[PDB]
Image 1 (cartoon, each protein chain N blue to C red):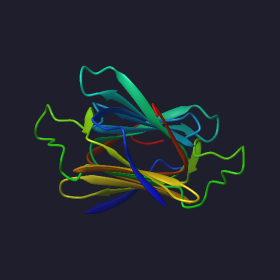
Image 2 (tube, rainbow over the protein chains, first blue to last red):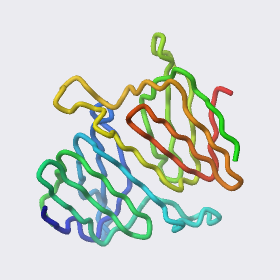
Image 3 (cartoon, rainbow over the protein chains, first blue to last red):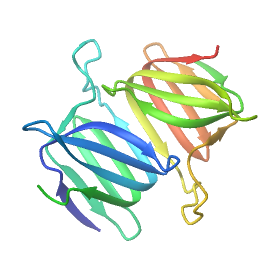
Image 4 (cartoon, chains in turn cyan, yellow):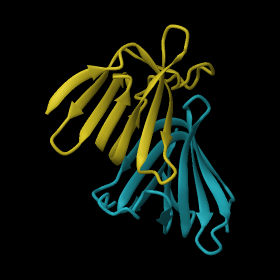
Length: 106
Length: 104
């Protein structure tokens, strides 16, 4: 069990299944120029939770999940799997056998 | 509250967020020869949960979530939102303000 903050001040713009559903990849831009920044790859998914937590105003036309601006992403490493937690009103939790990401730092 | 079983004997092959992320589309084939069957579109998502519950053997290099064979899907229509539940060991639950599907 370890904890670590990664991907400071990023913008999540997609969540994509791959490898016949076994992998989830989250892709991000930076919050300055807005260019592509990188990704978090969650391989061999254990669980995935998205809860909008009454945060998105669906009566608001201009309001939507993506792009989702994120101050930082919590990464937990256990003996046999890892978990990322995104908590920005909306909450996203993903547990997977391996979690890797690029780039390794800003 | 009205509960209903839909999409009998289907195979789920993708779960896709829209560009703005407000909509989730689940796409299905039949389980006969893999021809396209239809979709369930969940608009204005409230929550989405996928738990593989140790039913995908990751030590078996051949095992994978998709295609996910489904005997039926439970559809709940509450007063102000709807929910689908897929329970095949693997569990998928999606609540959204509206849930629409084709074919009817």
